[PDB]
Image (tube, rainbow, N blue to C red; front, side, top):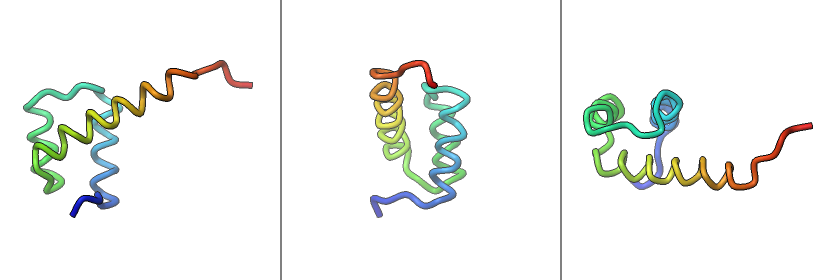
Length: 63
């Protein structure tokens, strides 16, 4: 549908840890392994990059 499964969110996040900016080869390989379309992978990484930067925007040393 438009939700992701649990395994999908695990493997999307695994890639994001290695590189915040997967190129076409990585994104294609992800879409094959998880049965998503390339377009949905691409958008998910645009979304996940903007989440990382929303969290950096008020990052502070932790107590």
